[PDB]
Image (tube, coloured by chain):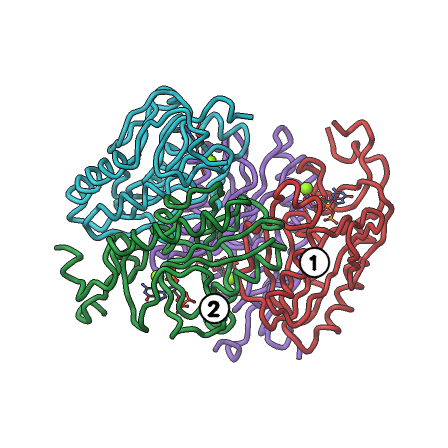
Chain colours: A cyan, B purple, C red, D green
Amino acid sequence: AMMNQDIEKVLISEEQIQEKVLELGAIIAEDYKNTVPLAIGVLKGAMPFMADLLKRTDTYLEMDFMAVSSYGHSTVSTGEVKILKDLDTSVEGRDILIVEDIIDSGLTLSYLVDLFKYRKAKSVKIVTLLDKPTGRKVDLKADYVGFTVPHEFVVGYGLDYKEQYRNLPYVGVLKPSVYS
Amino acid sequence: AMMNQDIEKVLISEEQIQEKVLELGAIIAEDYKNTVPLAIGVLKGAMPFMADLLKRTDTYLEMDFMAVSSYGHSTVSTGEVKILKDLDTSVEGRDILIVEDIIDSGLTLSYLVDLFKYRKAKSVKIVTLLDKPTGRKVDLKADYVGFTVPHEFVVGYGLDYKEQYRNLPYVGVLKPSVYS
Amino acid sequence: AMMNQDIEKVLISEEQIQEKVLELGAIIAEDYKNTVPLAIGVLKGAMPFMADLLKRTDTYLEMDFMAVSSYGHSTVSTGEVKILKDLDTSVEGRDILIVEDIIDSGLTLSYLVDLFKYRKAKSVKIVTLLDKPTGRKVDLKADYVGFTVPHEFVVGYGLDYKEQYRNLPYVGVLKPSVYS
Amino acid sequence: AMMNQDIEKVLISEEQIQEKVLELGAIIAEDYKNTVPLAIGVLKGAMPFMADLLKRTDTYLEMDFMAVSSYGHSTVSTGEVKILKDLDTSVEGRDILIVEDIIDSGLTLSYLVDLFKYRKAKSVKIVTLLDKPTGRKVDLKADYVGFTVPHEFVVGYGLDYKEQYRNLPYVGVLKPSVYS
Ligand SMILES: Nc1nc2c(ncn2[C@@H]2O[C@H](COP(=O)(O)OP(=O)(O)O)[C@@H](OP(=O)(O)OP(=O)(O)O)[C@H]2O)c(=O)[nH]1
Ligand SMILES: Nc1nc2c(ncn2[C@@H]2O[C@H](COP(=O)(O)OP(=O)(O)O)[C@@H](OP(=O)(O)OP(=O)(O)O)[C@H]2O)c(=O)[nH]1
Ligand SMILES: Nc1nc2c(ncn2[C@@H]2O[C@H](COP(=O)(O)OP(=O)(O)O)[C@@H](OP(=O)(O)OP(=O)(O)O)[C@H]2O)c(=O)[nH]1
Ligand SMILES: Nc1nc2c(ncn2[C@@H]2O[C@H](COP(=O)(O)OP(=O)(O)O)[C@@H](OP(=O)(O)OP(=O)(O)O)[C@H]2O)c(=O)[nH]1
Ligand SMILES: [Mg+2]
Ligand SMILES: [Mg+2]
Ligand SMILES: [Mg+2]
Ligand SMILES: [Mg+2]
C-alpha cells in the first residue's frame, strides 16, 4: 500500500514545481519590492505551494490565512461562502496577494477578491500554481500562473482526493480504479 | 451588594421598553408579511432586545447571529472588523433585518450593512432599540428606532460596562464613582 | 398565513414562561450572590430564554456565547462538535452557568460541560427551560430545570422547525401537516 | 532593501533543514504506515515546516489546521487559548500528529495536546522542527525533534518578528539594531 501505486501518470514532478516556484518567487519579489504585501492562502490546498513560493520570494512580506465553507446552493452559483477564520489583520490599504493551488470554477476566489476590494484593499492580485480555464464559471484570470493544465482531476502538492494525497511532492492523475 | 445601587438614574424603564418593543414588533410584522426575512443580531449587546422584539413580531422569520472583533486602530477609522462567526445561511436574495441594541458611531454597523449588500442581499434594514445619532462617525440611518437618547454612556438591557450590567431589565446611567 | 394557525396545541404559554423565568432568576441570583459567574448560551435556540432569565437574575454576571456545528457521525455518538465561535474570555477559575433552551440527548451539552472542566472551570452548572429525559443518550441532568416535558417535538421561544417559529412567545406542538 | 542584511548570523541553513526534514519524514512514514493519521499544523508559524515535512512523508495521511489567540494574561499561565478555527474533522479515534515550528514555553501546545486527548484521540504525538527546552514553562516533550536550539530568539522558515521574516528559507538571528 503505497501512494505512488495509485497514480496513473505524473503531470508535474517535484523538480519542475520547484523550478516554477523559483521563477514565480523572483518575479513576485521584484513586483512587490516597494511594499510589504499581505500574502493570503485559502486552506487547505494552497499551503504547500504557498510555503515553497514565499521562501523563493526575497522581499519583506506578511502571511495570513482564511478558512471558508460552502453554504450549499448559494456557493455552487455565486461563490458566496461562510468565513470560518477571517484574516488576523485589516485589509484596508494593504496590497493583497492571494496564493492558490488551483483555479477551476473561480467562484469562491472571485467572491474573496471582491470581498477584499470591498474592504478597501490597495490592490488584489492572484498567484496560482495550476489554472484550469476549462471549468471557469466566472470571468476570473490569475495575475501570476505557474502552469495551465487540462480539465483532468489531479492530486498532490496540496490537492486531495477525499483529504488524502495532499502530501505528495508532485502533481499527477489518479488511476480510475481509485475513485469510489 | 446589588447593581441598582450603582445606577444613578433610570433613563428608560422596563415598562417603557416593552411598550415600544410591542409597537416595533407589530410594525415589522406588517412590513415583512410577504417575505421570510433573516433577522440578524450582533453579539453580545443586541441579544436582550432581539429576544423581546421577535417575541412581538408575529410573522415568519429566521434568526441568525454574527460575532466580530476590532483590528485595533483600524476599526476606529472605517469600522472594518474581523468576522469571528459568520452567518449560518447565505445572504444572497434574502431580506436582511439587523437587530441592534444601540447605534453610536455606526462605524462597525455600516461595514456590516454594506458587507451584506456586497453579498447580494435583496434588502438590508436596521432596527435599533436606542439611537445615539450625536455620536455618528459615518452617515448611517436606522430604519426602525425605539428611542433616541442623548449623547451619554448608558447601561442595561444588553449594554455593558466592562462586561457587566447587561442583565438589567432597564436602561440607566451609572454613578460616576463606578468608572475606574 | 399566520404562525398560530400551524400550532395544534400550546404546551407553555408566555405567562407561564415568564412566571418560571422569574422563579429561576431569583433562585440563581441567590446561589450566585458571592461570585460573578460567566453565563453562556449555545446558539441559536437558547437566546430568548437566556435573555429573559438573566434580566430576572438580580446579581452581577457576565454573558458569553458559543457556536458549534456537527462533524457528522462523531457528533451523533459522542457529542464532539466543531467550535465555530469560542468564548471571548478564559474559563479557568470561572463559575460557568450554561443556559439552554432544551436538553434532549445531552450529547453536545455534556461535551461542552467537560470541555469547560478541562479548561479548569471553578464550577459548571446548567439551567435549562425544558428537559426531555426521554431522549437522553448520556447520564446528564440539569442543575436548574424550568419544565420537564414529554417526548414530543415542540417549537417556539427559541426552538425551531427548519429555522422558523423561534420567535413565538410560547411553546407548542406543530400540527402534523406542517412537517415535510 | 533586503532581509539578509537584517540577519546577524544563520543558525540553521536551508540545506541543513531539508536534510533533517528528509530524515524526519522517513521516520514518521514508517511509524504511521498502518494508520491514516491527522496531521495538524498550528498557524501561522508551522506552515513552512509542515509543507516540507509531509512532502517527505510517503504514507497516507490527512491534513488539517487550527488557529488560536490568547485571552490576554490568562494564556500566559495555563496556556488556555481561544479557538478561532477548530479542526474540520473529529478527533475521536484518530491518531493525531501535531506539526510545530518551535516549542518554547509549551504552554499553548500542551493545552491543545490534552484538548485532543479530551476529545478521545487514539494517540497524540508532536513533531517540531526546533526545540527550545530551556524555555519550558510546563513539562512537554516532543516525540520527534529536528533541531534543539539554544535559548535565543530566532526567525525564518515560519518564525516571525512582528509578522515578517517568515518567508526566509533558513533559520537565523536578527541583528539587535532591528528590535524596536
Ligand atoms: N484535487 C483537486 N481539487 C480541485 C481540482 N479543481 C478544483 N479543486 C478543488 O475543489 C474545490 C472546489 O473547487 P471549485 O469551486 O469547483 O473550483 P475553484 O477551485 O475554481 O473554486 C476547491 O477547494 P476544496 O477542495 O473545496 O478545498 P481544499 O481541498 O483546498 O481544502 C478546489 O481547490 C482538481 O483538479 N483536483
Ligand atoms: N454600554 C454602552 N455601550 C455602547 C454605547 N454606545 C455604543 N456602545 C457599544 O460600544 C461598542 C463600540 O461603540 P462605538 O464604536 O462608539 O459605536 P458603534 O458601535 O455604533 O460603532 C459597540 O459594541 P461593543 O460594546 O463593542 O459590543 P457588545 O458590548 O455589544 O458585545 C456599541 O454597541 C453606550 O451608550 N453604552
Ligand atoms: N425544535 C426542537 N428542537 C429540539 C427538540 N429537542 C432537541 N432539539 C434541538 O435539536 C438539536 C439536536 O438535539 P440533540 O443533540 O438530539 O439533543 P440535545 O438537545 O439533548 O443535544 C439541538 O439544537 P439545534 O437545533 O442543533 O441548534 P439550535 O436550533 O439551538 O440552533 C436541540 O436544541 C425539540 O423538542 N424541539
Ligand atoms: N520568531 C520566534 N517565535 C517564537 C520563538 N519561540 C517561540 N515563538 C513563538 O512565540 C509564540 C509564543 O511563544 P511562547 O508562549 O513563549 O512559547 P510556546 O509557543 O511554546 O508557548 C508562539 O507562536 P506565535 O508567535 O504566537 O504564533 P505564530 O507566529 O506561529 O502565528 C511561538 O511559536 C522564537 O525563538 N522565535
Ligand atoms: Mg480537498
Ligand atoms: Mg459593550
Ligand atoms: Mg434549530
Ligand atoms: Mg510569532
The relative height of residue C76 versus residue D157 in the rendered view (above or below) is above
The relative height of residue A130 versus residue C25 in the rendered view (above or below) is above
- Do discs 1 and 2 share a chain? no
Picture quadrant where residue C36 is located: bottom right
Q: Amino acid at mark 1?
A: Val
- Image mark for residue D107: 2
- Image mark for residue B57: none
Evaluate whether residue B79 shows in this view: no
Q: Secondary structure at mark 2?
A: helix
Evaluate whether residue B92 shows in this view: yes
- Chain for disc number 2: D
Q: Is residue C27 left or right of residue B26?
A: right
Query: Foreground residue, C178 or B155?
Result: C178
Q: Which residue is mark 1?
A: C99
Between marks 1 and 2, how big is the CA–CA gap? Answer: 30 Å
Task: Say which residue appears at 34% left-offset and 20% top-offset.
Answer: A150
Query: Foreground residue, C128 or B63?
Result: C128
Q: Is mark 2 within 8 Å of ligand 4?
A: yes
Task: Say which residue appears at 48% left-offset and 46% top-offset.
Answer: D64
